[PDB]
Image: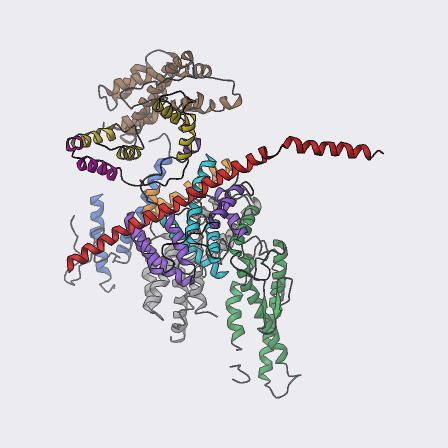
Chain colours: A orange, B red, C purple, D yellow, F brown, G green, H blue, I cyan
Amino acid sequence: VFRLQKFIDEFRTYQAFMWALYKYFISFKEELTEIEKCII
Amino acid sequence: AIQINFIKNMIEETLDDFREACHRDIVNLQVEMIKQFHIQSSEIQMLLERYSLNESLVSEIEKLREENKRLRANF
Amino acid sequence: PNVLLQNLCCRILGKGEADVAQQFQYAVRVIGSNFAPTVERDEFLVTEKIKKEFVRQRREADGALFSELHRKLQSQGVLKNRWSILYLLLSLSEDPRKQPNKTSSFAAL
Amino acid sequence: QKSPNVLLQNLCCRILGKGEADVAQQFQYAVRVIGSNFAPTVERDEFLVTEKIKKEFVRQRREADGALFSELHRKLQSQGVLKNRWSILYLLLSLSED
Amino acid sequence: MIHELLLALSGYPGSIFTWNKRTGLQVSQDIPFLHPGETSVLNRLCKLGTDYIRFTEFIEQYTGLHGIYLRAFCRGLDSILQPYRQALLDLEQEFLADPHLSISHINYSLDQFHLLFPSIMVVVEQIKSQKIHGCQILETVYKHSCGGLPPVRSALEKTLAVCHGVMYKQLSAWM
Amino acid sequence: MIHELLLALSGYPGSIFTWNKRTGLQVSQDIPFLHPGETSVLNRLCKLGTDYIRFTEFIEQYTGLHGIYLRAFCRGLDSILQPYRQALLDLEQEFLADPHLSISHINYSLDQFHLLFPSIMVVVEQIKSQKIHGCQILETVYKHSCGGLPPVRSALEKTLAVCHGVMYKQLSAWM
Amino acid sequence: EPYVTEAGREAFDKLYKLHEGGLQILSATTLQPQLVLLEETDLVKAVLNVLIGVVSSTFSYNQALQSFAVKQGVYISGTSPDNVSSLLTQVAEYGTYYTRLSHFSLLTVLDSSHSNGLVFQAFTSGLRKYLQYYRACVLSTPASLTLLTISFLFRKLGRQLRYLAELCCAFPTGVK
Amino acid sequence: GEASEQTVSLLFCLWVETVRPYLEIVDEWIVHGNLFDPAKEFIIQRNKDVPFNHRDFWYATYLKPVLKQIIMAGKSMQLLKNLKCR
Amino acid sequence: MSAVRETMDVLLEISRLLNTGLDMETLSICVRLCEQGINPEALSSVIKELRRASDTLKA
């Protein structure tokens, strides 16, 4: 996950593949707040 | 002249490390001096309280004073 | 000075506000013995000890950075008390290799 | 068991040649010594210490002893049950004699 | 934390959030009774409110070189701060709904913004380093909305749209 | 006792539970406080975690020689380990509901899985020491689910069902 | 337990007071700066007033700059750590340009002059219509749950007020 | 698959989003008869030849018949902007 | 007071690079002590002795 993040920097084919990885990340951060509410 | 100034400048690099190791050693040494005096001072303070007088005796002078006074505060 | 030296005794131990009495009185005694130093002032000489030390511990990059930080430091405000500050950080300098043995097993002695 | 103090009592007792309480005073002394603040001289390199020992052997003309020790160092490391080798090597260094 | 992090996010200096002019707004290092681990992500949360007041300064200089398209580019970009600021209002009621809110939802709402905000800063930075004026901005912003990242080409399409209207002021009176 | 063994059963090693990876397992009991009688049975439960980590290695290796029915049987077999693992966390709360339970409880729950675990591990090892691949893994497990033991013959019809389902995909497009 | 992030406001407040103290020792002044209670809902009413150009108990109007002055200390500043001490100054400054318009309109009436332009009077008849427009919008600022729902509301009127205030400042009169 | 649709969706997210700027250059290559592709990288190997007496030259490796429909269409559409139409 | 905030951010960089191991609150005490005047030898000597003492007390 740290490696996958290291690819995120700020052609388009290669940018839209990086953004498909990151669009997929907000659904893993969506889970992060689920499991964060059980433990708090 | 050239080699003399090369040897000179390296010897100084090494002597700086050595000076500072010795300097630190006096700081550590001063700590050891004072910490031992502090233990001892503490042993003595306690011992002179015990052997120089009877704690026993002073606490019985107060007791007889408390009893005698109270008896007299009913006369 | 008393409120400041004391607060140091509480913080370092992270606990105790009169349970640090022993350490306070001790700090006061130590400070009450008159040390004399090897070199008093000169910004360049203390800065140099810190540079050589950097090289010696293999933190060469950081040593490079420290020089930028030193110059920066003067510009955020000029210090009259720098030699002493820069020394204190010097004496607390450590090497990135090795541990100092155990000091959490040393208490039991 | 293996606490710092117990381990020290065992030292005194056997070396002085007497019982536990006959070495009681030197036991008190010993503790005072250990509890003295000492700052590490080794905070770097197992290698540099190994080199000093090798220097001791050469210095006394005990070259054969340095040739064997070098091989023995390599073994000592390899079994590696010691995690404070360096300290031990320093202790041995100070005990170097002819 | 909860109202206090909205107002570090606006970019304005706090005591806990020190401003050092070398770095912009950043959280000060290793503050006791907070593990150091949560401040690293917090430094990144400051990086979107640092570039946002590196942004109002690009506005206020030309509002309230010279160019009638400079202040037209100010009204291109303000609608990009419009969903931004709307998410600042979306966090506020969340904190009334519950005021025991942890910072991991706050981190999550802002990851949408993290690839939108340095990409507009780099845009204004190439503008201010070539010292551009007038109509030759619209071709620099056009090959920039030719850009990848789907939020960001739309962002750079709103900035394109407003100063193309000031081209239209000229070309409506000229024709 | 109990929580180190619950998680060495999931296949996470101890050092009082030595596992040296895929040449063998040593039980590693030189334990004073656990009795020579309660540790002797603890070795009997350990054999059933040895065969549990010889089975998950075959999962991760072929989902991640050649054949779509090796990895289709790998998504059949995880579904059968799904009540195994389900039972592993219900036991977690069993030791929190009262702390008056010991490893006698662990012997009692794990005999239901004891009639599943060598008997399926020998099936896949017989697949893999002949190097069987393709549609004839399904014939191999079919002639095993033609076999006996009432839990295993129902289980292997389920493991047959997900990768027969992958068969069903080829001949639906082929027709 | 909770860490600061989860722990609400109070934990953060205790922290802010401790941290500021740490800095406060090297700086020596008559009396150290301390907090003087306001609540967060009491701050949003002192700011409701400063938009019309009226003082509360955090604002001291200064005739020497014709501007308002907030407390500079560690004066309570919401639960923010001396952030409202800088943020509220930009919106008190937004309310300061509203008292310039009303200062200029009451002095450019010609029932106090008859040498200054008729046209000069005619700028005010339109100018006074933006002033009442402000007064219904200050009447519409509640609800305020934070100081942002209001500063962002006047983001749009702010760009304008700075132009529209300082065109007057030179001093153009008449046909000029 | 067919135990769950969740990893089918995961690979298709990466598939439909990587492919999308790579379709919309080809779409422009027809309806506008020209494409945006640098002179320092050629990224799909369709490129317009500068000469007026020549159409379009395909670069070689330095589904495939469906890619041939793109070559012949793009040839004819690169023409049609060059012609005056009726 | 503005001044007081800037100096500490640069100072904290040196101390953490050089290995010193003082939190924010304590780093402020020493700067006070050095401004009111202290021998540098004493200050280093105490800090080292308190640290050695603290770790043993805890354990």
The correct choice, above or below, for G110 with respect to G138 in the image is below
Q: Which residues are magenta?
A: D40-66
Q: Residue at x 15, y 59 (%)?
A: B2
Which residue is farthest front?
A: B52
Foreground of the two, B75 or G4? B75
Query: Would you place residue G101 above or below residue H64 in this image?
Result: below
Please indicate whether residue C73 sits to the left or right of residue G19 in the image: left
- Nearest the camera: H25 or C33? C33
On the picture, is F153 further left or further right than B35? left
Query: Is the residue B3 above or below the residue D4 in the image?
Result: below
Q: Quadrant of the C terminus of chain F?
A: top left
From the viewer's side, name the closer residue of D12 and A30. Answer: D12
Instruction: Say whether residue G114 is left or right of residue C11.
Output: right
Task: Give the dominant element type of the magenta stretch: helix, strand or loop.
Answer: helix
> What is the number of callouts on the image?
0
User: Where residue G56 sits in the image (x, y, percent)?
Assistant: 65, 63
Measured as percent of width and height from the top left, residue A3 is found at 32, 43
Task: Identify the image quadrant of the N terminus of chain F.
Answer: top left
Q: Is residue D61 magenta?
A: yes
- Examine the image and state in which quarter residue F87 appears: top left
Answer yes or no: is residue C68 visible: yes
Seen as rendered, the residue at the extreme right is B75
Residue B25: image quadrant is top left
Query: Where residue B58 sits: x, y (%)?
Result: 67, 34
Residue B3 in the image: state x and y as whole percent: 15, 57
Inspect the magenta stretch and tell me whether residue F132 lies in it: no
Q: Is residue A12 visible?
A: no
